[PDB]
Amino acid sequence: ASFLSSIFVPVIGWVVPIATFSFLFLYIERE
Amino acid sequence: KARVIVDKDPVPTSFEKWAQPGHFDRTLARGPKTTTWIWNLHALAHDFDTHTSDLEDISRKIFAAHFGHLAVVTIWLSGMIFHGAKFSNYEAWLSDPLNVRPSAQVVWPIVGQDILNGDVGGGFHGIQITSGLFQVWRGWGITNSFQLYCTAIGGLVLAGLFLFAGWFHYHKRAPKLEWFQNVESMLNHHLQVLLGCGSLGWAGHLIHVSAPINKLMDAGVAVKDIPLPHEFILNKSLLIDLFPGFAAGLTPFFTLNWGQYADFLTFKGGLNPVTGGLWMTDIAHHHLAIAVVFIIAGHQYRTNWGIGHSIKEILENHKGPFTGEGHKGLYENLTTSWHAQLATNLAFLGSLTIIIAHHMYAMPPYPYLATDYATQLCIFTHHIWIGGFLIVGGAAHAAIFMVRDYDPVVNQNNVLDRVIRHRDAIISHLNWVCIFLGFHSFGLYIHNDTMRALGRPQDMFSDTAIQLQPVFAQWVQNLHTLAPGGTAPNALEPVSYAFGGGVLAVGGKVAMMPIALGTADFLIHHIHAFTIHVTVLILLKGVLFARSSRLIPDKANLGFRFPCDGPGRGGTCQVSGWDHVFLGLFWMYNSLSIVIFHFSWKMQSDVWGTVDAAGNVSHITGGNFAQSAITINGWLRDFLWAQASQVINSYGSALSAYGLMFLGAHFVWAFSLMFLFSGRGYWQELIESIVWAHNKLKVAPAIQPRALSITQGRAVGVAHYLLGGIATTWAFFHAHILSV
Amino acid sequence: AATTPLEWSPTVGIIMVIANVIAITFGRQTIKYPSAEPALLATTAFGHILGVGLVLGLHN
Amino acid sequence: SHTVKIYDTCIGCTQCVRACPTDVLEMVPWDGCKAAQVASSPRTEDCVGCKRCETACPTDFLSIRVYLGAETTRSMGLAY
Amino acid sequence: LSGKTPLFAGSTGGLLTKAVEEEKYAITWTSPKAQVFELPTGGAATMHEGENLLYIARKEYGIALGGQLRKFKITNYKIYRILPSGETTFIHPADGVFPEKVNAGREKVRFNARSIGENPNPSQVKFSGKATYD
Amino acid sequence: GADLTPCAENPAFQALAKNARNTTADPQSGQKRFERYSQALCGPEGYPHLIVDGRLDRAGDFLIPSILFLYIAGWIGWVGRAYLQAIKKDSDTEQKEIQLDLGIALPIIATGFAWPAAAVKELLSGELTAKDSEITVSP
Amino acid sequence: NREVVFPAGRDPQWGNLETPVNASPLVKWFINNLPAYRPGLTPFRRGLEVGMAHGYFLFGPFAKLGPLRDAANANLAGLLGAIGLVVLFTLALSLYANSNPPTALASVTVPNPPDAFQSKEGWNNFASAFLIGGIGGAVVAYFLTSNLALIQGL
Amino acid sequence: QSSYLIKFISTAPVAATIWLTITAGILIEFNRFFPDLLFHPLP
Ligand code: CLA
Ligand code: CLA
Ligand code: CLA
Ligand code: CLA
Ligand code: CLA
Ligand code: CLA
Ligand SMILES: CC1=C(/C=C/C(C)=C/C=C/C(C)=C/C=C/C=C(C)/C=C/C=C(C)/C=C/C2=C(C)CCCC2(C)C)C(C)(C)CCC1
Ligand SMILES: CC1=C(/C=C/C(C)=C\C=C\C(C)=C\C=C\C=C(C)\C=C\C=C(C)\C=C\C2=C(C)CCCC2(C)C)C(C)(C)CCC1
Ligand SMILES: CC1=C(C/C=C(\C)CCC[C@H](C)CCC[C@H](C)CCCC(C)C)C(=O)c2ccccc2C1=O
Ligand code: SF4
Ligand code: SF4
């Protein structure tokens, strides 16, 4: 099942940073 | 109104003030309650402005202090030629300048250090020299030791005269403030006499002594067969045989028939094929043209005969629409503050010294200098460094003028006041430029360094790949190669073979060849521009913000040298104009260090190397610069790791001292990091515990010991950081090039 | 090939002469502080440069 | 924000008030028989915390300290 | 609030966006002469013979200026705090007497009757919500 | 003794002795060096090794140098301690520290050859140590 | 001739300075009539014109210099790579919009209040238009460059 | 006066330079006659 690396690697490099930094930036800037 | 005004016997000459220290200042004159008094004694010895406020007392110290400094330089210069007289191989070096290496230092047969006196050549055991004094004396037409022995005693005699002068002036005959303030007289004298007549005189020596003698020496005559200089003057038959223009005499000069002197006042502009070096006749025609220009130029100013310019009128009348009052008030600042004059003189003198180093390597002006790669490399590296230090000193005294001597009344809507009133825009854009260059100068290395590791050499910024060529410089190169004919028609050969043209070969060596500019030079030239802009940002910021900042409104009151102005407002650490100079020195060292590295690898890879009869030039490093200097690992591999083999393996040979100074230099660099990273607070608490042990055993010092001051700890570090740094590449440059 | 030089000729001296005269007329009006004692010695010197500049400059 | 606390070792030299950049400290009358003046810190909100008050105090150890705390625009020296 | 502006061409060093949004400051002074004085943020400026007024971004600029004014023998300098809504408050010489000189109306604040050695340890005061400097 | 042989009989030592590279101006400095080093112990590499065990068979290595140091070093400390104490009774103490009173110092430097006797005398009864209660300390 | 540089407005107290680059006739028109400051437009139309300019700009670097530039699918990589960058640019607007962005500033070149970017709605509508116009500009640049030989071949 | 000159010599640097040069010259001169001295040769 080598295709999983093609799906799980970029999720760690792109999806996880975007989602985490997106929520955090709104959380730290909340009022 | 130029006049000689003097005060008779202001200051006595007693030995009293020698004993009691701190006489110059009142705070230190009280007593040494603390060890910081010791460090403050040296830091305030030359701060004459702090000792007194009367400009007469300041200027008299400065004018006399210069004389004591000249004695040190004359003793040095006289000392160099003295070693050439007694302990040297110069007399043997002239017999064969291509097989005998130059040496003038001999270390005594004491513990293990006779090794340094290896077989340098010519039956002499001595340390090999890289200053190039041997080539200078040949340019001076010195062919025997007794001639050099006479010149050394003359310098020592001259040293006493300068030394007598500073005594005579500060103590017996002190000029008044008016004597120094007559600027218009000073500038005429230095341009005409010190530079003009000094240049005109040296033309006489070159024409009468150096050019004829060197013209016999390169021919192939023995050193003993050469007549002495006075023999040429008295016996004109010998002079006419070489340069027949002298047969006409001095009449062609006065009658404007100057073409008769074409034999020894040439404009060939190329290098002598026999001895790697410019033609003596071309150098002879140099200073004669320079002297006339300088003699004429110095008559510009008035100097008390109604004829000439007032510098105040020149500056005031250069106003404009954009600049409010133009250069009004600058003459007053420069005539009421020594630091302003010091800043201008230091900055442009340093840029001059860098400008020398670039001219000399491409246009070797001495005989057999180009073939001696060791002398050529250290000579370029030397003046490159000295110019860097002096430029940083210019920014320091520029800022010291602001805190100490700035008058807002004078600088009102002038060119300087208008500069301070938009300082934010100057730095914010320079900030943008520094970031832009650092990305697009260094990021291109990382892209190459990253791609080659990924097995993608096609995606690099290299000569086969995307290459960014320096088209602008290559265009300017071709204009110089074509200056023979057309523009500059009388010139036979270009000003330098670095721009282009044919190769020159002396013996088996190559003196100079065309320096091709490719993608590697395009990157490194931007790296230099990057590193130069940042130190300007650090230094220029200190000058503008020394008076005040948005953070600190009153920064001048604290002074030029204050550590922090408190820990609040976040943190105000290193906010002074002093600390900017401290930071700029690291960047000066960073920028300047790549320049000499750019010089070493390029000249070894592209320029220098053995040459065959068929013109095949076997370069030293084998042309590896183009495909390896584009990556950072290439420098680490091909330049540092590879060329340092001679240094580490120098043990058990004559170059062993370089391996020691090389290794020792890394220590002082790391020892610097004690003071830069740490802080005074920890060290005072450590001394507290140590003082307890002395109070226990009753070895307590009367002078209470304290840790070093804050600005001192920063000063002590950068002194080590630079000394340990420069000494490292100093030995690497020496041991590597001396072996090859 | 060296530039062609100049044998002595009386025509050369008239260029030096006229060069001095234009200098005297040029300085006498425009010099801010003409008299201090002088300027005659100075203005004649400039004419020698302009003369030597014209004299050698013409014949090339 | 930055708390400025004064202790009983004051002697009314007034050197702390003259050093304050932001005019945080103000001398006040000591009702007791010590002196006609002892320091105070009414406008503590403008304390940037440059410790100039402490450097000017002539005691063995300080009669006035500056205990740092929460930051604000006035304390951080921000003109923006 | 009244006065005349010091005559200077302008400068980047000066007022920024903070003034519109929150707490710009001002300083007022009166001088008999018209000298040249260095501004708090770079530059030089002249001063009129009556009721000079300058707007400054912070309180530190004013007292730093006031110290420079004392060199010219000017001791009547008043600093204000102008809020975005126009509310102005007279601050620096809060009473007619300056801070360095004593006035009877004032009261001591944040005074500890003990010496620094007498302060409690932090372990004696933890989780209570009080600090050692109290 | 550990992984070594006598220096006189070791082959590697004799190999280096032929090419000794005399240090001083004396021509035989190299041969004279290796002659004296034959007494010491040498390893496989050919260089000598010193044993600081304290055995009297090999005491010139460290033990004799050790005694010669401490007599010299205690001279410096006893002199400095006495010169500092004598100054403290005088009025201007700090200046005398910088500008040395050679009249006071050279008599002290003349002494110090008998520093161990004075050290024991101060230790048995005297001023070698001040009391802990009368010395500055942090809280 | 007389001075060219003046203080921002009548007040010299303020920071900004009137300069040729800041307050010339030509520069004031261009900047104030750019879509980010042009009068008489809604927040949606501003973002559309801005994105349409940027998608057309961002297609080039990916195509002619990115990987596979020397391949058949070079121009296709520029379109997909640009859209991925436009989406991140679109996402950034939504975060700056949904974080209560303070205000837009008024300088000398744009003396009036710039636009109705003073709320979350103005920035959110700007973001939706950026993606629509942004993807459009890249798609346009792809079809031209890919079919530029045909357009010249006509 | 000579009294002032003696005080100059008695200062910290000149006293240190004079003394250290003497201690240096002893080790320097002793090492040229007695070359190596790795250890004390024991009879
Ligand atoms: C850790 C995770 C990760 C992953 C999986 C990738 C993956 C990739 N990077 Mg990358 N990168 C990363 C982290 C990562 N990166 C980080 C942290 C950095 C900072 C240094 C970079 C910096 C970087 C640069 C500078 C470049 C890449 C490029 C690439 C691509 C090269 C593929 C190829 O063979 O040539 C290309 C082969 C092709 C067939 C064309 C690729 C077409 C793209 C990938 C299609 C993308 C569609 C897009 C997501 C559409 C979304 C729309 C939707 C949201 C509506 C590949 C997709 C290169 C590139 O140009 O990609 C375009 C490139 O130049 N990356
Ligand atoms: C003075 C300038 C000028 C120029 C350079 C042209 C040029 C042209 N005209 Mg034209 N025209 C002009 C003035 C001009 N006209 C005036 C003043 C009038 C009024 C009388 C006309 C009336 C006119 C008519 C009635 C027609 C033309 C047509 C044409 C094209 C015919 C070329 C051909 O041989 O067949 C065709 C060759 C080709 C290679 C195909 C051309 C494809 C077009 C030109 C591509 C245009 C794309 C365009 C730039 C998109 C615009 C958007 C952009 C602004 C962002 C040619 C491009 C003919 C046409 O149909 O063009 C399509 C046509 O029917 N013109
Ligand atoms: C002839 C003997 C003589 C005597 C007795 C004096 C006596 C005096 N001079 Mg004087 N002077 C002399 C010669 C002499 N000078 C000469 C030849 C010059 C010209 C250079 C001067 C220039 C001069 C100036 C400009 C000033 C004095 C001052 C003074 C007074 C204070 C000096 C002092 O205490 O510092 C004693 C300091 C030293 C002994 C150290 C001097 C170090 C020398 C000059 C340089 C050594 C460089 C060296 C090679 C660096 C190596 C570094 C490295 C190896 C470690 C004192 C009355 C000062 C004064 O009046 O104060 C108000 C003052 O401002 N003098
Ligand atoms: C023409 C050259 C020149 C001159 C005349 C001056 C003169 C002056 N400078 Mg200055 N400066 C210069 C160049 C110059 N500088 C350069 C090139 C730099 C950049 C590095 C500086 C950086 C600088 C700073 C940062 C400061 C000055 C200051 C001063 C003033 C007081 C300095 C003092 O007390 O001296 C005595 C200085 C010392 C005792 C320091 C000793 C440093 C040693 C020599 C470093 C060791 C180098 C050595 C070669 C190492 C090898 C040998 C060693 C291992 C034994 C004085 C007016 C100070 C000041 O307050 O001005 C108002 C000040 O703060 N300057
Ligand atoms: C190697 C060490 C190092 C580096 C990299 C820097 C970097 C910098 N210093 Mg510096 N500095 C250093 C050591 C260093 N310093 C030391 C030791 C000192 C003490 C003397 C100083 C003192 C100092 C001063 C006093 C000043 C600087 C300034 C600067 C900046 C210049 C602007 C520039 O080049 O653009 C930025 C360039 C870089 C950061 C180079 C590398 C960037 C690569 C190519 C890009 C990265 C790829 C990719 C985006 C990574 C993404 C990863 C992802 C997963 C997150 C820059 C941030 C100046 C400044 O800020 O002016 C603007 C300034 O005034 N420094
Ligand atoms: C900072 C310097 C720098 C530069 C110039 C480049 C350049 C490049 N890299 Mg690279 N890279 C760098 C640092 C750099 N790299 C670093 C530090 C790393 C390590 C992480 C890498 C790692 C890396 C990888 C792994 C890859 C590249 C690739 C590439 C290429 C494709 C670029 C691309 O698709 O971006 C697209 C860029 C954009 C969409 C933005 C462009 C911005 C434009 C130019 C702005 C212009 C402003 C304008 C002039 C001003 C307007 C004025 C107005 C008033 C009108 C290109 C040659 C790829 C390749 O294959 O190389 C051939 C690739 O796969 N890079
Ligand atoms: C001279 C000058 C200049 C220059 C300019 C430039 C350089 C320009 C830019 C350019 C650009 C930057 C361009 C761009 C453009 C773009 C376009 C042209 C776009 C397009 C679009 C479209 C058409 C789209 C559409 C669509 C949509 C929206 C959706 C759906 C799809 C479609 C496709 C339909 C400047 C100003 C700087 C300065 C001054 C002067
Ligand atoms: C005009 C203007 C300006 C300026 C500007 C400049 C001059 C510049 C900029 C610059 C910039 C701002 C730049 C940027 C760049 C970026 C880049 C360089 C990026 C790249 C990226 C990449 C390469 C990635 C890719 C991708 C994606 C996106 C997704 C998927 C995956 C991948 C990886 C494929 C200002 C601001 C003032 C204002 C407005 C106007
Ligand atoms: C080590 C260190 C110190 C302590 C360094 C000290 C105290 C240096 C001491 C230098 C010499 C050793 C002082 C004593 C010299 C003797 C008087 C000489 C004896 C005489 C014989 C040599 C002849 C600081 O004070 C400091 C301050 C700020 C930042 C970093 C640091 C820092 O790193
Ligand atoms: S910390 Fe600074 S601002 Fe606060 S009272 Fe002390 S000196 Fe004044
Ligand atoms: S002790 Fe300190 S705080 Fe008290 S009056 Fe004196 S200087 Fe001010």
Image (cartoon, coloured by chain):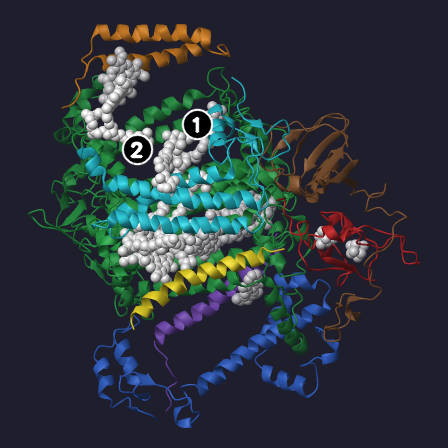
Chain ID at mark 2:
B
User: Which residue is tagged 2?
Assistant: B202
Q: Amino acid at mark 1?
A: His
| Image hue for chain B | green
Query: Which chain: yellow?
Result: A
Query: Which chain: cyan?
Result: G
- For image coordinates 58% across by 41% down, the residue present is G118
Query: Which chain: orange?
Result: C
Q: Position of residue B235 (x, y in %)?
A: 18, 30
Query: Which chain: blue?
Result: F
Q: Would residue F98 appear left or right of B253 to someone viewing this image?
A: right
Residue B546, quarter of the rendered image: top right
User: Which residue is tagged 1?
Assistant: B189
Residue G2, quarter of the rendered image: top right
The answer to whether residue B134 is seen in the rendering is no
B126 or E72, nearer to the observer: E72
Q: Position of residue B735 (x, y in %)?
A: 27, 60
Q: Amino acid at mark 2?
A: Trp
Q: Would residue D44 appear left or right of B69 to someone viewing this image?
A: right
